[PDB]
Length: 442
Ligand SMILES: O=c1ccn([C@@H]2O[C@H](COP(=O)(O)OP(=O)(O)O)[C@@H](O)[C@H]2O)c(=O)[nH]1
Image (cartoon, rainbow, N blue to C red):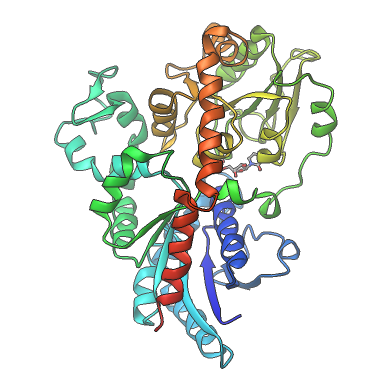
């Protein structure tokens, strides 16, 4: 292959997944692929015989928990010299007829821009969160001087934000609840994304059409929107063993009778709220498949606080599944999600309507957009209460009053499918991306 692309993900599941989906999309278009990766949380290299892996940067920190994410600031602050040596030696060791076209990194690797610059290597960024999230980010000054960033101030919560009517004030509070902490790294990510040679968004035009103008205005480099879950699932980059019972169980369930439930990799709840969630599921009387990661419940290894047989025959709790493949199964009627972007987009691409909870960061923004703009789910935006949970589940899955949500999800899946076909917005965006990358050396 004449042209090689180097991709460098952040080593967590929700960041590895889109990068390796993109790597496959680019390999399909004729590029050779080198993955730079930490030894930490490395994927199964034997699932990618067509890729070359080069392990870097970590050849005392915990492997799990919120402290695991400390690797990202540390590598941003201390990895430049090593990344440069690794990039330069690969650039030098290339075949006579081969050329390294560009580096693609997670936007969170803001340190890679100066490194790539110093080698005259173009860097493109893969955004793993939405255009709407970015639009909210760049509106933070206007939020600030309206005081919305004031955790000890608790007013106008249910009001729409002025100048940003798609959001409520509480959404902004929740999303930027750690602002004073994160404003530094957030600012660096945005700066070095704007300074990049191109931004790839895991999205599609018909999903976030209200946001395109913002990214054209705010980012000089070209933007490309590609809905990676419509190209392929992320099953090959799973860091955990998929549960081997769920599909046999799903085959025993009537169509659209199952609520899939997963609250995310790092989310955490009190025992009180955990039990209230369980009560709401039982009260809904719907069948459910619930992925609970060990540690989800404060103070318990897994799901100890659940009483024996409390979930009855209608429910299953597992630790890990191939999520997009589950969402594609005919038994699934709805998805109760924490509103992480991969999960939300997977559900959209499989046409599954959603019930939304959130645990901060971009999740409240995703829930608000999907529930109020697209109207493909119900946002539980006032905590955990068994009656409200049961009503939301049933509205999406059973009630005739929720038909519009179910139909809106079906229509949006069809729009994603159309965007991939020749002539569609995603197809042409990918065509532009391939031509752009191919042009970078001339
Ligand atoms: O049992 C599970 C739970 C999650 N996922 C995948 O893990 C990723 C989770 O990313 P997301 O952005 O939704 O949220 P996070 O867990 O990073 O907060 C998605 O690709 C899911 O399909 C999976 O394959 N199986």
